[PDB]
Length: 231
Ligand SMILES: [Co+2]
Ligand code: NI
Ligand code: NI
Ligand code: NI
Ligand code: NI
Ligand SMILES: [Zn+2]
Image 1 (spheres, rainbow, N blue to C red):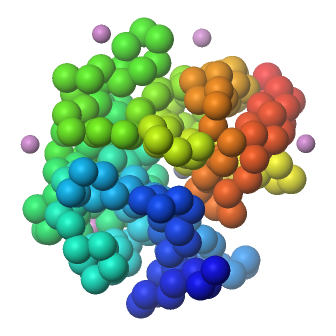
Image 2 (spheres, rainbow, N blue to C red):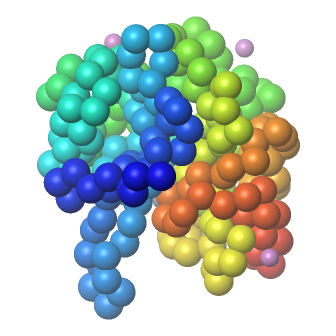
């Protein structure tokens, strides 16, 4: 290979010829730098972004890395729930003219979570799939609401043309010792929601998540099995 690229305070790992993971870091007192991962997808003369970094300035650095390494307009960004690690850098997307999308419920939750809402709301059909009219130009991003889990609003994304699915903070890796921050969790539905994400992207073999390296479908099984203990 070539290694994972460092650009300002971020790290970018290429996962497929048109997909990269972005990683940004925040110090949390007690246990050092906490990585948060999102995605970057090159499609049909544009770039799509999934999740912000923790901060505006870090998010502005993602845009700069895109401009330097890819050099295609960012058509849109989708954010996967209203917490700092996924939505902390909304202001930087908006300053850069980028159309932003989140679950309607994430936009309703954003103020109480201290987040800036996306500019557009996604709504989801009864079977969990995004309503296409509310997700124009998403191209290969297939967006699915699996039910409440890590938060009430958490949504997940598959990348058509690849073996990649992104569970965001709903899914922990296959050796995680707990389900992490449950302050906003739905402990009743968590397990079913994790299993629904797995059934929605049944062919995905690389599962990207918010706080560690990409794992296999074992991350989904282990997560659901941990969530079973909560209900
Ligand atoms: Co801000
Ligand atoms: Ni608009
Ligand atoms: Ni419909
Ligand atoms: Ni229910
Ligand atoms: Ni396990
Ligand atoms: Zn979260």
